[PDB]
Length: 77
Length: 79
Ligand SMILES: [Zn+2]
Ligand SMILES: [Zn+2]
Image (cartoon, rainbow over all chains, first blue to last red; front, side, top):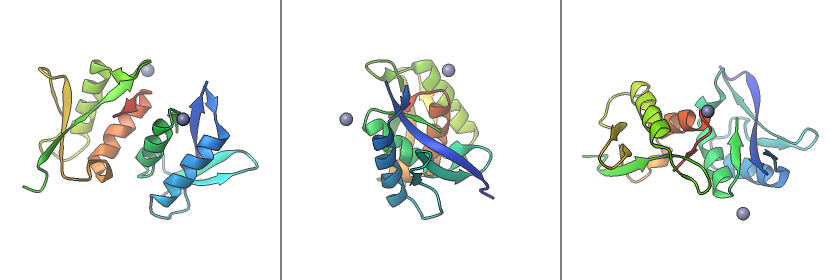
């Protein structure tokens, strides 16, 4: 059922801010069930999450959006 | 009964971020269509509110996730 990798980005300026994106990724990981999603990977600077054909159907998407917009970022799925 | 609080679900745009009434109404309608009917997700013209009926943890519920899906697909900021 969740066989697609997506990168959630928290953008400013609009380009990803790696520090805010990592923080949001970590906060999302801690505030969602542990399913493999919401692990920030340094090599390609991606907050990776796992989903189906629509990334925004993942339950963590709204959590990511809450933290990203709290810090005045624009979330991109 | 068990969902006794009214929340306004907003999809915001601009600087400063303010509700866009048309996108909010569209998202409210799409959310209504894609959730089970429980009284939520009716857009009220007199106060320009997409009214969401919930309890104490409105943002943990499945309907809010659907609102968030549509709002962010159109590049809004939900609440
Ligand atoms: Zn800040
Ligand atoms: Zn658009």
